[PDB]
Each structure stands twice: as structure tokens, then as C-alpha cells.
Image (tube, coloured by chain):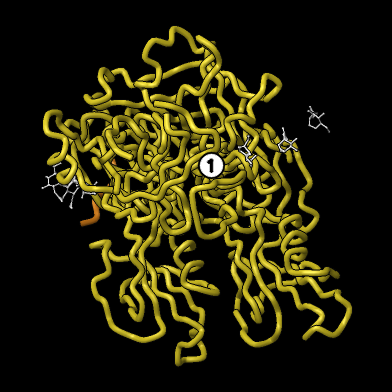
Chain colours: A yellow, B orange
């Protein structure tokens, strides 16, 4: 894919729409997440056009997937990242000086700094972007004022140059927000509020995921296929209120209602729908019809066609006919079926071109039941065994892959290690006896230890290892998600410790499901030392720096690093990862 | 409340 840009050219026509971005770099992001945009042309601030044309980001589509380039001054061209394979990010940390971004201004307040204004935009349930007037701002009553804004689209309706001010977006899409997510879904309930948009969705999960990435959706109501009125089945309704909560909860039957999860965006699948919808046909415009042996094959053909947004496979019906079906690659103006017909024999789903906009640690992992305690390859693919070469190479502790180049582990693990260079990170491991001198391993380039760290019992017990070579993900090696700051009040109830017991090591990996126990309950058992909010306990066979991983809503979260346990009775103590999200992110980008 | 913009001066 043509990843970088194209000063100073311009595509000819094919326009879907026109939006305003503070930059081509961002224009290219809007183009990526737009469901039809394949390419675009941005217009930078320049002598060549009136102010009213600056910052114009024009999204475009072409059937051949490209357009006629033409030379033009202060135009910038590019392609969407849909075609690309590596991760795709909405996050934009840019502050833009002397730029003022227009929208519905809903809050005026005073703020220390552009930074602390950003913190406020990010922490607010409505905020798309802000403008902050600096203390050098001519008008004495406007100095230090943090103005909070939103629009229909999430992008400003207008951009203007204005001395002595700075704008920027909500860092909700880097996992920076403190706003709590409401994961609770209310069955048989409709909401009433400003309906800001609407789509057809095969179920209330797709409905909720769409609500989440729709800039102006705070909550939603979904009308199931069993809804009385024919005209509104599978209608997914995208709502908002000024309160921001739904004013009212009306009872009913065969609707379902819930909230945007935009706050918990990483750590939840959003842009990725990998389910198949049986005896379901998704209406849209047809892009192709091809032969294929299965839906899985259909989905792949869709996924590999960049204009494709969803498909329907009609198989060899019943069990009779050649096992060759028809794959209808379809598309719409908004990435959804215009209509969802049940009972016509088709099998339907969506493109996976979408799926790399999601955090890698949100893929499913292929299960089994029931126990216990024998683990196997594939099972805990974030678990690493962290080796020391001296005195002689041996398991020093456990850790967890959280990044392409990152391990999260316990600080206390590196008591008297003078140098990164004595460390070996091995992934994919089960048996310890499987590691040999020929075994492949990652070198650690660096060790970051919470600076306020001292005694494990004192807390701050957290380390990042930056690996020397990145990890190529696989069924054996995959990151695990950090909890979301907006999940603070969540109640995990499927928790597991993994490791080799390090003290006297064990050969194969151990797995033990255990239960969190409240801080109070812990505080009561650990007489002497305090137990800060920055810890978390469990109990009722993992090693140091090892993961306390909890499964919630189909995704694994790294809830705790093991730090000081007297347990397997008495509870173990752990670093409370959620409390160090800011820190990890700062340290890692 | 809806607030007005910042001054152009
Ligand atoms: C403009 O915001 C003020 C700051 O409070 C934050 O603003 C948003 C991020 C929103 O999420 C809000 O819930 C945040 O707490 C807000 O006033 C609040 O804080 C100030 C002091 O900074 C104080 O004057 C006020 O009493 C505080 N309480 C509440 C909940 O607002 C202010 O009200 C808001 N303007 C409005 C609502 O008109
Ligand atoms: C782990 O331990 C021993 C190696 O001596 C072996 O008998 C056992 O089957 C091993 N498991 C796997 C999956 O290799
Ligand atoms: C990453 O994906 C698989 C891992 O098995 C491999 O085939 C491929 O070559 C790897 N690396 C790159 C840089 O594509
Ligand atoms: C734009 O177009 C031409 C190709 O026609 C390119 O080589 C050059 O950079 C630009 N044209 C001129 C006249 O400089």
C-alpha cells in the first residue's frame, strides 16, 4: 500500500464527502476509518487558496481503487491504510498552535495548561476536541480558558488560524481516559433521547460496537429480529443526551439497550466482527459474485477485496448440490447492510480488512475444557519465561508480552542484576526442559523500573523490559490487554495465575484459577504492612512478575503482576496494573 | 449552555 503521502498532487474527483482536518496526516486517519474512503486530498494553509479552503480534507472512492493525479499547489494526497497489514491507530496526540477548531462549544473553564485542558477533554463524555487560549492571549478575560467542543462527525466543522491559541483531540482513543465505561447491557429496554443516527445490525453486539466507534453515540437501543413492527427489525439506534445518560428506561420486549464503550476502546473488539450469521442475508450493493466452497472462503475473498464491507454466501443448499456456493461481495455507504433478511438461506458476515484497527490482544484464543493443571502450547500465549545466564542460565522469573517489543514484570525481579545483557526472554514455552542452547530467545535492550520502587512490600513493584527484537505474533506468542482505566469498578470473576512456581521450579507451565479478594479482606490478613489501592490480592504455583490474568467478556486482561505472596492459607499480593496504566503508556508509546 | 467562540480581536 502507498503508505506515505504525496505533496503536492491532487486526485481527480470521486468524492464522497468533505471534512476538516488540522493535517493530511490526520486526514489519512479519517479516510482510513471511513467505511468507503480509499484515498483523499488535503489542502494545507497556503497563499494559493482563500483561508476558507485551508484544512479541507476530501475523502474519495474509485472503482479501480485509484484516481488521476494532478499537480496542484499545497494539496496533499494519500491512500487509506485499509490496504495495509500493520496496526492502524486513531490516536492523535498532536497539539496544534495558532489553530482553532470549530464546533459546538459546550463548556468554558479555566485551566493550568493546554495539557490539563487535554486531560479534561479526554475525561469528558462529550468531548471530541478542545481549544485553549494561552496566558499570552490578548483578551484578558479569555486567557487560560479551556473551551470544549463536539460535532456530529468528531471532526471540526471549520478550522481557522488564530494567534496565541492551541487545539487538539480527545486522547480517548489512546487508552488515556478516566471516564468509566458501562459494560452493562439492559435487555427488554428502550431508551428515548436524541437519535443521532441509525444502522441495521444483525445483533445487539454489533450494534454496541458500532455505537462505540460512532463519534456522537453515547448509548443505543437495538430492536431484535423478533420485534413486532416489521419495518424496525435489526434496526440499531444511535442515541445521545446532554445529561449524557439516557433520561429514561422504558420497559419492552425484544429491544436491548446499552452504552458507548469508547472509553474502553483497546481491550475490546470494536471494528471487528468475525461471527457468521446463519440463514441471514445482508442487503447492499454488489461488487462481485464468485464461486466458493464455504463461507470461511467467502469471508476471505471479501477481506481481500478492499472495497468489500460485508458478504453473503449462499451455499449448495441443503446438502445436495456441488459443494460450490456463490459468494456475494457487497458494500454500502456506511459499512452496514441496508437491510437484513432472515430466512433466505444465505450465510453472512463482514470484512476482516477491518480487524487491524482493533487491538491485537482482542483476538479470540481457541479453547478447551476443563482442567487442569496440564497446560499446552497455544493456551497462555502472553506468558514468557524470563531467564538469567548467571550463575548458570536458569528461570529467573515470569512476565507477560504486552507489546511488540515489551514485557511487563515485577521490579523486585532484578534485585542485583547489573545489566540487561544477562537476561533471556523465551516465549512459546511449556516444558522448561524444552529450552536448549539452540532454542531461540529475545534479548533485553533495557530495564525500566518504577522509579519510586524500593521494597516489594512497599509497593510500586513494576518493571518493563524493552526487547531487542520485536515479536512476530502467533498462536504461541500474543499480547494480553492492559485493563482499561475506565474498567476500574469492574468485578473480575474468571482469574488465573500461570507460571512455574518460582522457591523451587517446576517443569511444565502451571495453571490455577483463583479468586480476587478485596483489599480490606487482605489488609485484615497482612497485619504489619499497608496495602495500597495500587495493589490487589487473591487466593483460595505462579512465579514472580507472573500474570494475574482475568477473562472478561471474551478478552484477557493483565490485572496483576505477582509481587509478594505467602499463599499456595493466606492471600497473594500483586501490583494492581490498572493503577499503572498512565505510567506504562508514558514509558512505551 | 452554548458558549461563543474565541475573539478574532
Ligand atoms: C465545565 O467543566 C467544569 C470542570 O469539570 C469537568 O468538566 C468536564 C470534563 C466534565 O466531564 C465534568 O464532569 C468534569 O468534572 C465543570 O465544573 C466542575 O469543576 C469546577 C472546578 O474545576 C467547579 O466549578 C464545578 O462545581 C465542578 N462540578 C461539575 C460536575 O461540573 C463545569 O460545570 C462545566 N461547565 C458546565 C457543566 O456548565
Ligand atoms: C513436559 O515434561 C516432560 C519432559 O521430560 C514430558 O514427559 C512431558 O510430556 C512434557 N510435555 C510436553 C508437551 O512436551
Ligand atoms: C511473521 O509471521 C509469520 C510467523 O510465523 C512468518 O511466516 C512471517 O515471515 C513473519 N515476519 C514478517 C516480518 O513478516
Ligand atoms: C508534475 O508533473 C510532472 C509529470 O508530468 C512531474 O515530473 C513534475 O514534478 C511536475 N511538473 C513540472 C512541470 O514541474
Residue at point 71%, 47% (across, down): A83
Q: Is residue A396 above or below residue A115?
A: above
Residue at point 24%, 40% (across, down): A570
Residue ranking furthest to the right? A322
Q: Is residue A186 left or right of residue A476?
A: left
Q: Is mark 1 within 8 Å of ligand 3?
A: no
Q: Position of residue A475 (x, y in %)?
A: 64, 45
| Closer to us: A481 or A369 | A369
Q: Position of residue A224 (x, y in %)?
A: 47, 81
| Closer to us: A360 or A166 | A360
The answer to whether residue A589 shows anywhere in this view is no
Residue at point 52%, 45% (across, down): A361
Q: Which residue was labeled with disc 1?
A: A89
Q: Position of residue A346 (x, y in %)?
A: 71, 79
Q: Is residue A515 left or right of residue A29?
A: left
| Closer to us: A14 or A379 | A379
The answer to whether residue A186 shows anywhere in this view is yes
Q: Quadrant of residue A341?
A: bottom right
Which quarter of the rendered picture does the N terminus of chain A lie within? top right
The chain identifier of the residue carrying mark 1 reads: A
Q: Is residue A284 above or below residue A103?
A: below
| Closer to us: A62 or A356 | A356
Circle 1: element type: loop
Residue at point 60%, 58% (across, down): A35
Neighbour tally class for label 1: few under 14, some 14-19, many 20 plus, Cα within 10 Å? some
Amino acid at each position: 500500500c502507498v503508505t506515505q503521502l504525496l505533496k503536492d498532487t491532487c486526485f481527480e474527483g470521486g468524492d464522497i464527502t468533505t471534512v476538516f482536518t488540522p493535517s493530511a496526516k490526520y486526514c489519512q486517519v479519517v479516510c482510513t476509518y471511513h467505511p468507503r474512503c480509499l484515498l483523499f486530498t488535503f489542502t494545507a494553509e497556503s497563499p494559493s487558496e482563500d483561508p476558507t479552503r485551508w484544512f479541507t480534507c476530501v475523502l474519495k472512492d474509485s472503482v479501480t481503487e485509484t484516481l488521476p493525479r494532478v499537480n496542484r499547489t499545497a494539496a496533499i494526497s494519500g491512500y487509506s491504510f485499509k490496504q495495509c497489514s500493520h496496526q492502524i491507530s486513531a490516536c492523535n496526540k498532536d497539539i496544534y498552535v495558532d489553530l482553532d477548531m470549530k464546533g459546538i462549544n459546550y463548556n468554558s473553564s479555566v485551566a493550568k495548561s493546554a495539557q490539563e485542558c487535554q486531560e479534561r477533554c479526554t475525561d469528558d463524555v462529550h468531548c471530541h476536541f478542545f481549544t485553549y487560549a494561552t496566558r499570552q492571549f490578548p483578551s484578558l478575560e479569555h486567557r487560560n480558558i479551556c473551551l470544549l467542543k463536539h460535532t456530529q462527525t468528531g471532526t471540526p466543522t471549520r478550522i481557522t488560524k488564530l494567534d496565541k491559541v492551541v487545539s487538539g483531540f480527545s486522547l480517548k482513543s489512546c487508552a488515556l481516559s478516566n471516564l468509566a465505561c458501562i459494560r452493562d447491557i439492559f435487555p427488554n429496554t428502550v431508551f428515548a433521547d436524541s437519535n443521532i443516527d441509525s444502522v441495521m445490525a444483525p445483533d445487539a453486539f454489533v450494534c454496541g460496537r458500532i455505537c462505540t466507534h460512532h463519534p456522537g453515540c453515547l448509548f443505543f437501543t437495538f430492536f431484535s429480529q423478533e420485534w413486532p413492527k416489521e419495518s424496525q427489525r435489526n434496526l440499531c439506534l444511535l442515541k445521545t443526551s446532554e445529561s449524557g445518560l439516557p433520561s429514561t428506561r422504558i420497559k419492552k420486549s425484544k429491544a436491548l439497550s446499552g452504552f458507548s464503550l469508547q472509553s474502553c476502546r483497546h481491550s475490546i473488539p470494536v471494528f471487528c466482527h468475525s461471527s457468521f450469521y446463519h440463514d441471514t442475508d445482508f442487503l447492499g450493493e454488489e461488487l462481485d459474485i464468485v464461486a466458493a466452497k464455504s463461507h470461511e472462503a467467502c469471508q476471505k475473498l471479501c477481506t481481500n477485496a478492499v472495497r468489500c464491507q460485508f458478504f453473503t454466501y449462499t451455499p449448495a443448499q441443503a446438502s445436495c448440490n456441488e459443494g460450490k456456493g456463490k459468494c456475494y461481495l457487497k458494500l454500502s455507504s456506511n459499512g452496514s447492510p441496508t437491510k437484513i433478511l432472515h430466512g433466505r438461506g444465505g450465510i453472512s458476515g463482514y470484512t476482516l480488512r477491518l480487524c487491524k484497527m482493533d487491538n491485537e490482544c482482542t483476538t479470540k484464543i481457541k479453547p478447551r475444557i476443563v482442567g487442569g493443571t496440564a497446560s499446552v502450547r497455544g493456551e497462555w500465549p502472553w506468558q514468557v519465561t524470563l531467564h538469567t545466564t548467571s550463575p548458570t542460565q536458569r528461570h529467573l522469573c515470569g512476565g507477560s508480552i504486552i507489546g511488540n517489543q515489551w514485557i511487563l514484570t515485577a521490579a523486585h525481579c532484578f534485585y542485583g542484576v547489573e545489566s540487561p545483557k544477562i537476561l533471556r526472554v523465551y516465549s512459546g514455552i511449556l516444558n522448561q526442559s524444552e529450552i536448549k542452547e539452540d532454542t531461540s530467545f529475545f534479548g533485553v535492550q533495557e530495564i525500566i523500573i518504577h522509579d519510586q520502587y524500593k521494597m516489594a512490600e512497599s509497593g510500586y513493584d513494576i518493571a518493563l523490559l524493552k526487547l531487542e527484537t520485536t515479536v512476530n505474533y502467533t498462536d504461541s506468542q500474543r499480547p494480553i490487554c492492559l485493563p482499561s482505566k475506565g474498567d476500574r469498578n469492574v468485578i473480575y470473576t474468571d482469574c488465573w495465575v500461570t507460571g512455574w512456581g518460582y522457591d523451587k521450579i517446576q517443569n511444565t507451565l502451571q495453571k490455577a484459577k483463583i479468586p480476587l479478594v478485596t483489599n480490606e479482606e487482605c489488609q485484615k490478613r497482612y497485619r504489619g504492612h499497608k496495602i495500597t489501592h495500587k495493589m490487589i490480592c487473591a487466593g483460595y504455583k505462579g512465579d514472580s512478575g507472573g500474570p494475574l490474568s482475568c477473562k472478561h467478556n471474551e478478552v484477557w486482561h493483565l490485572v496483576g503482576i505477582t509481587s509478594w505472596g505467602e499463599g499456595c492459607e493466606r492471600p497473594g499480593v500483586y501490583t494492581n496494573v490498572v493503577e499503572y496504566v498512565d505510567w506504562i503508556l508514558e514509558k512505551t508509546q | 449552555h452554548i458558549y461563543p467562540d474565541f475573539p478574532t480581536d
